[PDB]
């Protein structure tokens, strides 16, 4: 097989800067003494992959010329000249010169932008979940940057770790932010024995945490 | 103007078999090469099959003798028949039209190879506490719990509330997924105007429309 | 490449 080794794995880049992505083959591709069928695809969050470049350096229709493919021997490069927020996602190289067709492992392009604090909300368990014997308390932490953030759950002023489930969105292709949802799950029986439930969000933007809470009465 | 829609994904036991379809429009199938490419849970892309415009069939060795690509140019559908399914066949399967220096991929259909039971979601409303405060923007949500397999789709007011939505990726715990979705609207519009999360789970043929009611 | 061309060489 033709093995494609793609680097880097993650590529953080600021708006208007240049990103370079490299793909290294295990052999010379040229089919016979004809064309080299090396292609570049982008997958944006929530979408399917789309063609950027074919035969090493041709732009697919409607791809702007700030996308530029080159390469020779075993090294192929995709250069993105003036990165916009919408360029984020996972880039793959691909060869179709020899069967089996193969892809590089991918490069995740991430946009750097200004720091932004999350907007935090808390939600008590619904009466219909209580009925079935479980109790989930939810914090949304919306639209922040950078991605890294910590949530600490407190029940009556003391930390709880067991039963926390956290999930981040991909990076938003508009404002370049992340959001995350944190869910503390307990039994109805344990939920009914405590009053105050708190999530505390700690994040680069403040030395003090953002604290949201409610009382079970 | 090209459309491709894949269908036929869902759950299937190791050893079982499944037939995928790709339903094509705005072009004649026969004039293009049609392929299947899958994306694994680790986000590798892998080529799985091609059929040229002239009808030659091409497969990698990892699926040879198990997978069959075919087309029906009367219904304008391309198929992938899979058998002796294994765990490593778990992936999102895309249908791809190729020709004339162009590629166009459908939205994908998810195939999960697993022994776990098909289970519909429980959908729980997330409404602010009684004593919470105004802000002028109010955030509401939906918690979608206990289902298998992926995917579920979540919309708000049937797609009418599309901005200010964050739908969080599902996470697997045990043999069960959990996901949530938030929506943010002006406080002048809620509760005066209804906000309902619409959850569909095609593998159990289930839809839940949960209205978010203010508490107490 | 059948991903971009109708036949393969």
Image (spheres, coloured by chain):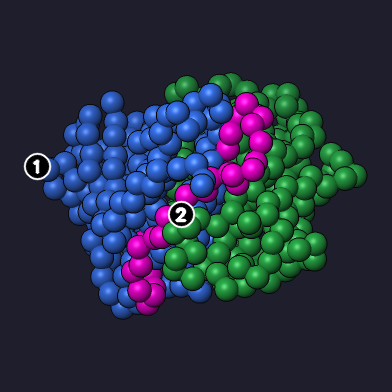
Chain colours: A green, B blue, C yellow
Residue B22 in view of the camera: yes
The residue wearing badge 2 is B124
What residue is at 47 percent from the left and 22 percent from the top? A62
Q: Along the line of sight, which residue is nearer the eye, C7 or B174? A: B174
Q: Along the line of sight, which residue is nearer the eye, A148 or B89? A: A148
Residue A105 in view of the camera: no
Rendered-image quadrant of the N terminus of chain B: top left
Residue B196 position by quadrant: top left
Asked which secondary structure carries label 2, the reply is strand
Mark 1, other Cα within 10 Å: few <14 / some 14–19 / many ≥20: few
The answer to whether residue B150 is left or right of residue A1 is left
Asked which secondary structure carries label 1, the reply is loop
The answer to whether residue B36 is left or right of residue A214 is left
Marked residue chain, label 2: B
Q: Which residues are magenta?
A: B111-139
Residue B43 at x, y percent in the picture: 53, 55
The residue wearing badge 1 is B74
């Amino acid at each position: 097989d033709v093995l494609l080794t793609q680097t880097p794995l993650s590529l953080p880049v600021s708006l208007g800067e240049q990103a370079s992505i490299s793909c290294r083959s295990s052999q010379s591709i040229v089919h016979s003494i004809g064309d080299t069928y090396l292609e570049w695809y982008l997958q944006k969050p929530g979408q399917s992959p789309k063609l950027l470049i074919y035969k090493v350096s041709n732009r697919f229709s409607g791809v702007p010329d700030r996308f530029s493919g080159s390469g020779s021997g075993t090294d192929f490069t995709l250069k993105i000249s003036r990165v916009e927020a919408e360029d984020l996602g996972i880039y793959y190289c691909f060869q179709g010169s020899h069967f089996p067709y193969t892809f590089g492992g991918g490069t995740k392009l991430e946009i750097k932008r200004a720091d932004a604090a999350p907007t935090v909300s808390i939600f008590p368990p619904s009466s219909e979940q209580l009925t079935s014997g479980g109790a989930s308390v939810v914090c949304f932490l919306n639209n922040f940057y950078p991605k890294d953030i910590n949530v600490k759950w407190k029940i009556d002023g003391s930390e709880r770790q067991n039963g926390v489930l956290n999930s981040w969105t991909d990076q938003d292709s508009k404002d370049s932010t992340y959001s995350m949802s944190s869910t503390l799950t307990l039994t109805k029986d344990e939920y009914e024995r405590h009053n105050s439930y708190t999530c505390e969000a700690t994040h680069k933007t403040s030395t003090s945490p953002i604290v949201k809470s409610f009382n079970r009465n | 103007q090209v459309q491709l829609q894949q269908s036929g994904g869902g759950s299937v036991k190791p050893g079982g078999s499944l037939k995928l379809s790709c339903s094509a429009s705005g072009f004649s199938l026969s004039t293009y090469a049609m392929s299947w490419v899958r994306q694994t849970p680790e986000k590798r892309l892998e080529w799985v099959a091609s059929m040229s415009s002239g009808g030659s069939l091409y497969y990698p060795d990892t699926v040879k003798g198990r997978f069959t690509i075919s087309r029906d140019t009367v219904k304008n559908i391309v198929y992938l028949q899979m058998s002796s399914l294994r765990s490593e066949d778990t992936a999102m399967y895309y249908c791809v039209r190729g020709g004339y220096g162009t590629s166009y991929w459908g939205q994908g259909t998810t195939v999960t190879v697993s022994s776990a039971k098909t289970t519909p979601p429980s959908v729980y409303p997330l409404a602010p506490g009684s004593a919470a405060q105004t802000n002028s923007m109010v955030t509401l949500g939906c918690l979608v719990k206990g289902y298998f397999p992926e995917p579920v789709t979540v919309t708000w007011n049937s797609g009418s509330l599309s901005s200010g939505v964050h739908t969080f990726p599902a996470v697997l715990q045990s043999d069960l997924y959990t996901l949530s979705s938030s929506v943010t609207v002006p406080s002048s519009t809620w509760p005066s105007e209804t906000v309902t999360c619409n959850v569909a789970h095609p593998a159990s043929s289930t839809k839940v429309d949960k209205k978010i009611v203010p508490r107490d | 490449s059948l991903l971009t061309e109708v036949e393969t060489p």
